[PDB]
Length: 131
Image (tube, rainbow, N blue to C red; front, side, top):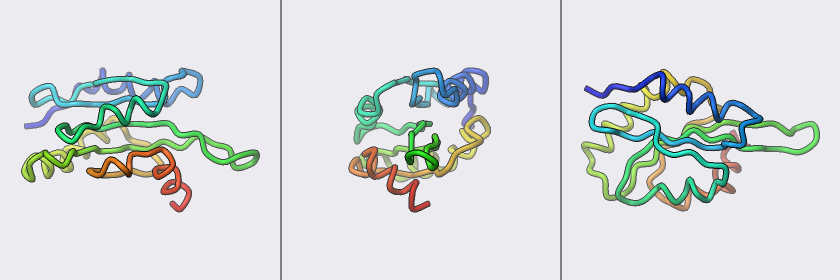
């Protein structure tokens, strides 16, 4: 029965899509059976800190990539599912990212991550470049 607060989540998505907003990441979390916005940040290290081994969340992140001609923003969807989350809830989260993408429609790449090392900016950015 997962639901999403589309108006509230859209505002968070739109915030990161605004190149001028100074907000480079937003999270979405479960409030019971509804996915709602969580946190916002300007500093990527503060995103990593939200991703504990005990929680599941979705994140939409603006990365600045390239240089000169190749400079551009690339957006990522990250579904973080900490290693202590049960298999049943891990599967439900990965099903539910389809619903999240009714709001988070446009992205360069999406990720499903349970190893904290893969949240590092340098990793995500190397995956975006390969990609």
